[PDB]
Length: 99
Length: 99
Ligand SMILES: CC(C)CN(C[C@@H](O)[C@H](Cc1ccccc1)NC(=O)O[C@H]1CO[C@H]2OCC[C@H]21)S(=O)(=O)c1ccc(N)cc1
Image (cartoon, rainbow over all chains, first blue to last red; front, side, top):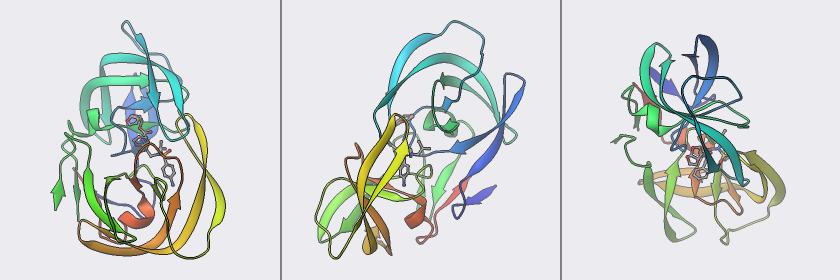
């Protein structure tokens, strides 16, 4: 689909059997989601936004279904104010900016 | 143009007679730039994201040329680690997500 940016580009995602809404964020290198439980072993990391940094838990090779499109990749879990789909997963569903 | 997201969507902008590179950020509601001089009056504001908040100076009706696309709108000036073109200006140049 083609999403215009008059409203936030919010889409529905399915991850770990749960439904959520996430923000298609071209400004985010990595996908970051609010607190939740996920499989596999995770390792610490720190990511920086506009107001500093937060501590997240990095999960690799995690399946996400973004508005119907499936993708497997890194997912960061931490105290983000918004669920964010970063470029690490946007490239997999073949998303592009166009103007 | 069509911009893929394998690399950060950095583009060339032209504001206040200066040349810079900015991040086409669909996750950003409004445009935020690093410190610089701009014309006219401004008002204090605070914007929040991953990590917390920063104090910015809001300039209204500021001319920017994004990849050769002219736009006039709100421009926030503050300690952002990256120059961010937010949705407030992406809409004016006809930017859309497509997958
Ligand atoms: C976090 C979003 C809900 C909103 N943000 C835009 C977002 O693209 C930021 C904007 C951004 C871009 C680069 C550097 C700092 C902030 N990027 C970001 O947080 O990504 C982080 C998670 O993955 C990593 O990728 C880069 C930073 C990490 S924001 O910076 O806080 C913001 C909020 C409001 C306005 N008007 C302008 C910008």
